[PDB]
Amino acid sequence: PRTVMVNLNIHSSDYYNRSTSPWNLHRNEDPERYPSVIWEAKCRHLGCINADGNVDYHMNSVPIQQEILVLRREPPHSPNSFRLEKILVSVGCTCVTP
Amino acid sequence: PRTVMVNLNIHNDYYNRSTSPWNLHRNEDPERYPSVIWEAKCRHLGCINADGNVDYHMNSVPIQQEILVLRREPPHSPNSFRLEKILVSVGCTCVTPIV
Ligand SMILES: CC(F)(F)c1nnc(N[C@H](c2cn3ncc([C@@H](C4CC4)N4C[C@@H](C(F)(F)F)NC4=O)cc3n2)C2CCC(F)(F)CC2)o1
Image (tube, rainbow over all chains, first blue to last red; front, side, top):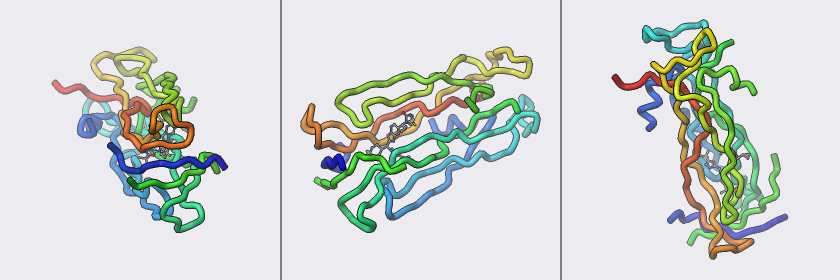
């Protein structure tokens, strides 16, 4: 264990609507985790929006997955003690050539 | 102060075909945890078309997200931190510019 003290008191999105692989945000909630709420990107379409403004299936919208560190309550249900943990979160969508 | 204890011992390529591909840039700060953060930098100003050529009628833009980091408090402290928000680039997407 490398135990440290953390003080939790801390001292654009509408532009991504113009993406050829647009996404919406999905609420992910876990009361055993900090941050408990994580907004996860879900691609709106299987294809990408082409020059005509239409969904084109010759290209694919794919979620960008990132490794994210979160705090897991340790022991479970502990309000003040945690262990660092890695999870995968979707942070947006990009358009790929299959 | 909302002081909590954190155990820092972690429990636990595809996007190359993107029309708005990106590379990773090393962001290092010895006063922060994680000290090293890899940020996405868009490879091109435009988006890659069907022919494999850059088209400047569209733009590759970095997706900026707010993430939480630990700042050493007091400075240089090996075991005490304050939570802090920073803005990082987590990938690139292709956008149709405003006309
Ligand atoms: C909104 C949220 F997703 F819940 C969220 N916000 N911050 C976190 N987690 C915070 C957080 C910060 N980072 N910074 C870097 C990384 C690494 C991944 C290889 C491990 N990445 C991911 C990628 C990107 F950051 F650019 F995305 N590039 C990287 O180098 C993960 C990460 N996790 C977390 C909150 C608890 C804490 F303070 F104790 C510690 C830090 O989650």
